[PDB]
Image (spheres, rainbow, N blue to C red):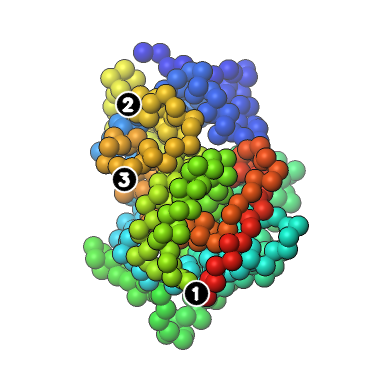
Amino acid sequence: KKMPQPKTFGELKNLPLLNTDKPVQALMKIADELGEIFKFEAPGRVTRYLSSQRLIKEACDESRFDKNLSQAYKFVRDFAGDGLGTSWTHEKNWKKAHNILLPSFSQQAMKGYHAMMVDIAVQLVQKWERLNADEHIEVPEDMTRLTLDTIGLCGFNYRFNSFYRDQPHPFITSMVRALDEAMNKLQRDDPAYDENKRQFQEDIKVMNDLVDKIIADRKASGEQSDDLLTHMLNGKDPETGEPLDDENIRYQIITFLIAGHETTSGLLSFALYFLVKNPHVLQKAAEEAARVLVDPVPSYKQVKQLKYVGMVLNEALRLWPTAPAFSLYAKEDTVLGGEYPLEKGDELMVLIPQLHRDKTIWGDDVEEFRPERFENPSAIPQHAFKPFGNGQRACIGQQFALHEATLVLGMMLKHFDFEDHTNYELDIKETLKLKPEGFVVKAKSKKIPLG
Ligand code: HEM
């Protein structure tokens, strides 16, 4: 069967379609008009975008398809290196890090991070408790402060102290600026790109300089903490028997911050947006938080008892998965969906927001925010809900992100009533991840002691 394809621009094929502020949202609108699969060509490049559960279930077959590094993540690799996210599955350091790091990211390993997550969540609550009557909350901005600080604390026992400042830590500043440059190179040898190829190097330096010092500092001290750095400095891969070397440990810490901060911040921001736009759902979630969070400080077990809050987060991830696409390649020649022959090496993109709007899986009301869709998670078919990727290349931080977001949203709902005082119109800014730009609320304290 012949594959649909969106509009072309002569010798540029489809490439100008992504020369836009909102490429994923453009790709979603194309999927709306062309259907479950469409070909996307560029000068010397071909990929196929998948939007249906019927095809994505095959793409998630790890015997047939492996993770591909997209063009963007090849540029990210210039400072993320061969950390988990930007390494190929067949690279020795991927499987080593995967085996060493998976125990540090278990649902059960969250018990050790809980106290430091509470540390940063308390700072967030206290900041909002301390706002004056006339004042409002910049939601993604504060969620990003929380998630970056939480990864820094739980990751390598480092305090970015984001709630003490307006201009971020020089590391954070230079990371985002480096991520920006990596993104900008998507639409670009020529000597006009000489200053862009000089500033990139400076941002890589500050990130490398500080994390390497931290690792050197910890090796010299020999101190043992509850962070991922300790586990990485003492872990051994059961298969090779080898530990990670210091350079790869550096890339892993850079990777935790790239991979975790924007997605989790976006999730919290989208979750609060849907709550203020659905007051009946907010009330049901607030009643749960009040019922369950009976102590001044949330316990690890209390966070696990926040069932509805977790459903709220999963429904937010259904509508706006904050890492909205992943890339695959065919391991061998194969036929997709019984009608699309693929050659070894052919690339696929999974368009996750469109998968999550497949009316054959979720029903006709896919645009509605309904947390009750997740009452029984086992009813959802295989590969129908994939906000954390697929298989052995799935998000290693899934339990970390969901524990942090359930804790923080639980505390938010316990301690404040929220007002959508501007009747905010959703505006989704796209970097490599999604976030509701300009989202803003008020929050009136329920005056509950906190500690
Ligand atoms: C709501 C929050 C998050 C979302 C939606 C998310 C999404 C994803 C997705 C879709 C992938 C697969 C990417 C691909 O196939 O190319 C991935 C991979 C990854 N994520 Fe997350 N992520 C989140 C939070 C986090 C956090 C908190 C961490 C903490 C370090 C993290 C670390 C990673 C790593 C290391 C990988 C690569 C894993 C591997 O291939 O071995 N993520 N993430």
Sequence-first disc among 2 and 3: 2
Across and down, in percent, residue 179 comes to 60, 51
> Mark 1 Cα within 10 Å, few/some/many (few <14, many 20+)?
some
Give the residue at the far bottom of this rendering. Answer: 221
Give the residue at the far top of this rendering. Answer: 1
> Mark 2 Cα within 10 Å, few/some/many (few <14, many 20+)?
some
Q: Is residue 440 left or right of residue 5?
A: right
- Residue pointed to by mark 3: 391
Across and down, in percent, residue 117 comes to 47, 67
Instruction: Mark 1 and mark 3 in contact? Answer it, CB < 8 Å.
Output: no
- Residue pointed to by mark 1: 157
Q: Nearer the viewer, residue 376 or 56?
A: 376
User: Disc 1 versus disc 3: distance between alpha carbons?
Assistant: 30 Å
**Residue at x 36% of width, y 48% of height:** 394
> As shown in the figure, which amino acid type bears the numbered disc 2?
Arg
**Residue at x 36% of width, y 13% of height:** 1
**Residue at x 38% of width, y 26% of height:** 363
**Residue at x 33% of width, y 42% of height:** 375
- Residue pointed to by mark 2: 54
Residue 411 in view (yes/no): yes
Q: Secondary structure at mark 1?
A: loop
Q: Nearer the viewer, residue 156 or 144?
A: 144
Q: Quadrant of residue 60?
A: top left
Q: Quadrant of residue 420?
A: top right
Across and down, in percent, residue 310 comes to 40, 50
